[PDB]
Amino acid sequence: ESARREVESQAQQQLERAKHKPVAFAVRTNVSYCGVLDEECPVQGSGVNFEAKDFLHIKEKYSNDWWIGRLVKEGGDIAFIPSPQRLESIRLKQEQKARRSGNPSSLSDIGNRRSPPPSLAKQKQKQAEHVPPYDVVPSMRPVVLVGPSLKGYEVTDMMQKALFDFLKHRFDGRISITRVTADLSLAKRSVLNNPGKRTIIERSSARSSIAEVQSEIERIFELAKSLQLVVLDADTINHPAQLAKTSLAPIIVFVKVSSPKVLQRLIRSRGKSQMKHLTVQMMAYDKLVQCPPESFDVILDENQLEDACEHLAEYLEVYWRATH
Amino acid sequence: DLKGYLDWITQAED
Image 1 (cartoon, chains in turn yellow, brown):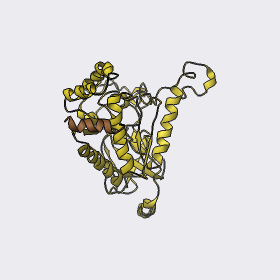
Image 2 (cartoon, chains in turn orange, cyan):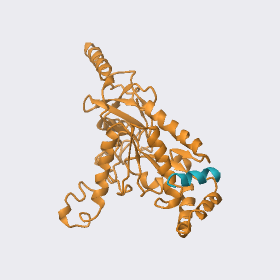
Image 3 (spheres, rainbow over the protein chains, first blue to last red):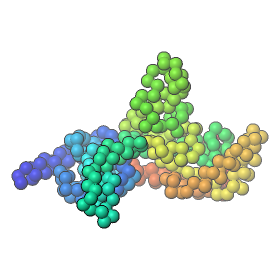
Image 4 (cartoon, one colour):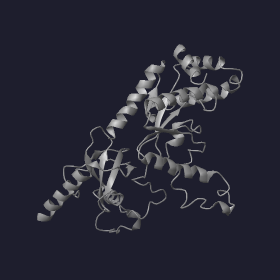
């Protein structure tokens, strides 16, 4: 076929020409699929072998069924990612190879109950939750420091502030750090079409601060669109589970004390205004370490400042190189 | 574990 070979040359030429163009936006996957095994790809052999919970970058537009993208790994080339409708179509192909998909069981019962597949056997139903396979996540995952206890107290604030200072100085010219006083745990996507569109409604949500929470969500996306590294300084985060179900998916960096005895001796030497909060502070210390390590992204358990700083720096440096 | 977590916890602001 002369049509497939000619469109192959044009597609390859487009990839070479577009290899030096700015990145437009990014999405996040949640299903295990391969971009090479599919026979509908316009270019064969240049697919992506991605897995569940992977990050892809999109630069230009191809069509309503396919897109051009590249991985976030070091030295990642350009691959093709199926469209959400195409992924929905290929999801239906995964559940059709089975013997049955609707109500009629095939337990040696053939010839009596035909039972044509109703709407319950298609994608029209099962819309109670309808988790989207593709989500419009920010262009990069933000960096957040959490623990070992609640923020706003003396024991906690300098440790992140000094760590922010080291990140700011080492990444001079490529860092943009801002303090978000608004809440970040209420970043929802399937609540309503437009919750509190106007502030003059004088409703429960119109007069509340919820509209401020969602307004800051788009600010992060635009800030992440600048390609510069961003670290959030919010003090409304105490557990990765509160931000786990959000679309931000930040880099959960956990710094922890080696022993509770070490922490309970640091609080004593701080000042009389801090032992009043010792009881509540110790509550967060035990509940945060009870979270499994795999929930967090990178751990900071070193007892020396120099050991942890470059341990975190190399994780951030490799991300900068891999995403370029 | 205490010496490294005491100077750093105070020198950031003080």
